[PDB]
Amino acid sequence: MLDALNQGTVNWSVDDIVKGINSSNVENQLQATQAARKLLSREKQPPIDNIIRAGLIPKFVSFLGRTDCSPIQFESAWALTNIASGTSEQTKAVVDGGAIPAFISLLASPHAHISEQAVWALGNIAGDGSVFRDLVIKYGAVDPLLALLAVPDMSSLACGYLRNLTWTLSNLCRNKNPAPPIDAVEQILPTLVRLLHHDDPEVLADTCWAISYLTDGPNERIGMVVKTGVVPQLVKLLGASELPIVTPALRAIGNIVTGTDEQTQVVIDAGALAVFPSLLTNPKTNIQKEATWTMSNITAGRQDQIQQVVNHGLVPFLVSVLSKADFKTQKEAVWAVTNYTSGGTVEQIVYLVHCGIIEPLMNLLTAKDTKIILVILDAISNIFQAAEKLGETEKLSIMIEECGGLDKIEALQNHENESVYRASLSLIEKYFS
Image (cartoon, rainbow, N blue to C red):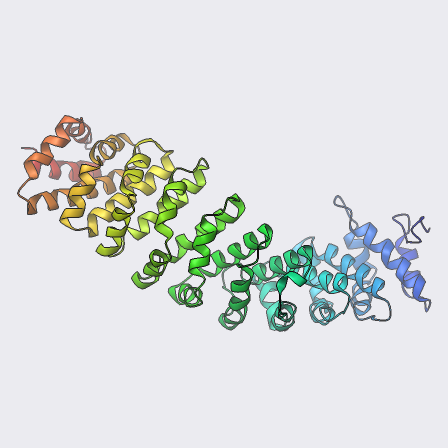
């Protein structure tokens, strides 16, 4: 019944656990609790419902408060968490048994490894959905969670512990319907901001993820993030060599430029455009895709913003990706071109055409995707409008003819797709007759 660690074992019955856990002997209570966490920590087929049916949750929860015996606090935190990591109903049973406030009080243990358990517990529950997340917040988890990081140097804290607390904060930032209560976000941001200057790769990755969640919302949310001055540091991390940093850094920058024109300018002012050559030629196609998407949202902005895209020499990269990247990225490149031609100046559209946008664009008119064809034709239209202003519609017509583009446009003349038939007929009637 005891192993060579003097702990309870997986060989204890529920009968045994119930007896031990109800004893006045503290060592017996601890062994019963160890036997329970060992049973419940089996990855596969843990007998969670048997422990719940033995009415044991309220007892495990009161053990969380047993300062006289930190190992009992640890072992019961562990068991409860394992229970909570099960079905939604199993989690709901842990919560209904009062575990959240008890975990929150446990953050005050002067034992790092105990307060660490509480952080871990609350992270698990918070991430079990928006509803639990809000319960964790409503019960007051935020203040004590942050107080653990209110120290002079974060580096006084062990890497493991910091990783664990950062992970838990990012779950308080995660999910929608509904999104995190705004005042909790206000409270948390300044700490995330300090975390982005820490130099542990996993801490940085977790914090970038949290920021990406906060920036996935209405502009009010984007603004809050932007107003902290993190954007520059986010841009620095875009440059990081670690893909697990670059990926959420990129998502966050991508989200921010879906915001207002001023919000996008903060991104440009921080020097993001300079990182785009390495992103747009990054072997990971997901990065190319996210990067091109971001670029599509910058070329949807103002003319002096489009001008910075040009000034950083990014247009040939865009041509390159429109030509010879995987299709999902090519779709973002179509958007980037359509946006750029929708808002750019005449001179900017002349430059885009001199970079050789036309052939790659025309080639995509064989795509079997109606949305994409209609957008490409929209882009074609915008380029023609600029040629009108120079009285050069005809020289563009000729550029389109020679790279096989008039053929691809003629090929859309099929009534089976009435939408595509009309778009393409009009274009043919106006500039190819």
